[PDB]
Image (cartoon, coloured by chain):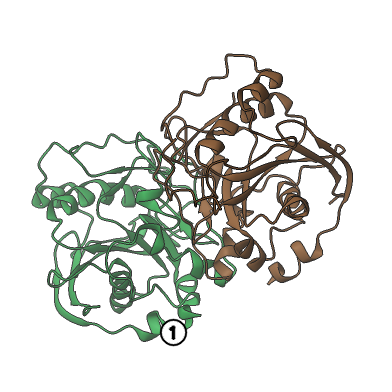
Chain colours: A brown, B green
Amino acid sequence: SLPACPEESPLLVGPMLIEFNMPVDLELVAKQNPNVKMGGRYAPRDCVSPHKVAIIIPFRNRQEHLKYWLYYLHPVLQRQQLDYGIYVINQAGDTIFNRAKLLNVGFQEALKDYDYTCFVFSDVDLIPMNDHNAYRCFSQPRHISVAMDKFGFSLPYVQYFGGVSALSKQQFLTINGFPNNYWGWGGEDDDIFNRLVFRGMSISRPNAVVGRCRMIRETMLSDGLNSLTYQVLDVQRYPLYTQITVDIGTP
Amino acid sequence: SLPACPEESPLLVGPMLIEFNMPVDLELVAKQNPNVKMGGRYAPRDCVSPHKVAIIIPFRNRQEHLKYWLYYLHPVLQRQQLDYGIYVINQAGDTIFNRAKLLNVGFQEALKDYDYTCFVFSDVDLIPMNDHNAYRCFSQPRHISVAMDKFGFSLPYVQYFGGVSALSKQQFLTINGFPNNYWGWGGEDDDIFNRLVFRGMSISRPNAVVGRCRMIRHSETMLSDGLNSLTYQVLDVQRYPLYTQITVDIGTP
């Protein structure tokens, strides 16, 4: 019935100022984005998007950062004319953090809501400075956070495929998702760039200016999606996001 | 007879001023480094170095840049107490450039002079700003150019394992060297990161400050495409005081 959305959205505004010297009230953010449905779900009214994107945020005790993330990304994602939903994967307990495992949980859980075909894995503390940085999938795995605010050496904050990146369902399934046994922060050695290589994939990215983000301030075949185990303890449908609280075990 | 050189050389000075305004005369540079022998060869007089390093530069019509590279790196390499030689691999003709294939030639040709055990592959237009950045090999593949001088975003110039990197002879042979069929400038698409992964190796590097480099300016297929399938024709070999230049025909796409 509806027409397909254009290939490039005409609603983009380009670079935007990101400042964190202003308190955020999510009740106001919700009234500013009234087309977002309960649970953080949105689709264009005027056209059909081919981008069915689940944005997955690994999370634990970062509510202030999340307020800023929602305040800044909901307008961006709509301007990009995406058919998206927001899934916050909250790691229950005080175990060592396991980013990769939570991303696997988010993939499995988001698919219970809707047949997403693209998955954006995003740290809660990275805001894109230009809405030309598409939050969706490409013919190759996509690295969305390319460089940081002040355009310095960026590998510490984003590694090769960290910070914000995107994988289609097929790309995610080809590598059997992320590993589940990397507890803690391992740097550019725990980057799953290795998994993309084994399956003959490379990295796509925008240019470093469009890709700027600002900060709020083998074993593969057996360790991954097919061996994932976890227990969901809570699911909360807030106006602007879904939060899933899970027990992912211990190292 | 001689003692082993220390693990860290006592001659290191740390950060360095790098400027590209003074014209360079290689006859004067040779008089500044009188211990460098014909062909750009040096070994310490006072100790035996465990680092037998061939520095291989893929090259074509960049003589001005090459002057600066020699002016700045010969002092650095000597201070690092290395047993090294300088090999410039000049691609004959003005065909489309093939960085990776030239690197394979340099590895094969350097070994005809001397039994090097470490190979540093360095773009001619990258100068290290700190002599603590070791131009030699490690237990894992080594990425020497980590970050750029000022605007630190470095991925376009260094990729994952480009710019300046080092592979021991064993590490190089394990991945069957570099590919030979990547014609042109491919960026991080021509990067051999996949080959290191395929063989269960990772990247070692210094921290981004020690690893800072400045750019000269004024502004499956692995097992079958590599060293074992390399073909080329040497057209000239010239032995200058400060470097060996090998001019080769590496064919066309």
- Locate residue A117, reporting x and y percent: 63, 57
Question: Which residue shows up at 25% across the image and 46% down it?
Answer: B72
- Locate residue A80, reporting x and y percent: 50, 41
Task: Find residue B92 and report its image quarter.
Answer: bottom left
Query: As drawn, is B75 to the left or to the right of B136?
Result: left
**Is residue B108 in sight in this rendering?**
yes
Of residue A142 and residue B86, the one placed in the foreground of this image is A142
Numbered disc 1: what chain?
B
Q: Secondary structure at mark 1?
A: helix
> Which residue is label 1 attached to?
B224
Question: In the image, what residue type sits under mark 1?
Answer: Ser
Q: Residue furthest top?
A: A22
Of residue B243 and residue A89, the one placed in the foreground of this image is A89
Question: Which residue shows up at 85% across the image and 57% down it?
Answer: A229
Query: As drawn, is A135 to the left or to the right of B14?
Result: right
Question: Which residue shows up at 75% across the image and 48% down it?
Answer: A102
**Is residue B1 in sight in this rendering?**
no
Number of residue marks: 1
Above or below, B44 against A207 in this view is below
